[PDB]
Amino acid sequence: KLPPGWEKRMSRXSGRVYYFNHITNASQWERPS
Image 1 (cartoon, rainbow, N blue to C red):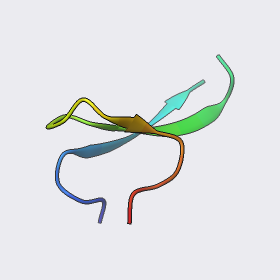
Image 2: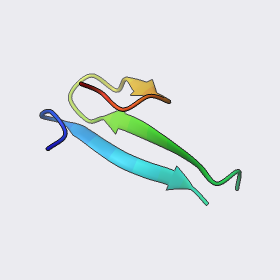
Image 3: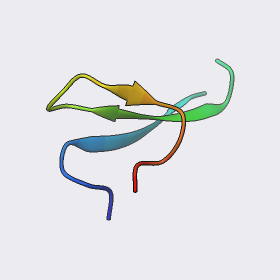
């Protein structure tokens, strides 16, 4: 599973997947380990 707080999203816009963290407000293109 994704680590705590992380959600996989897609901007169906560009079709790019990204990840967002609810705890920290961080976002990143790559899947968290």
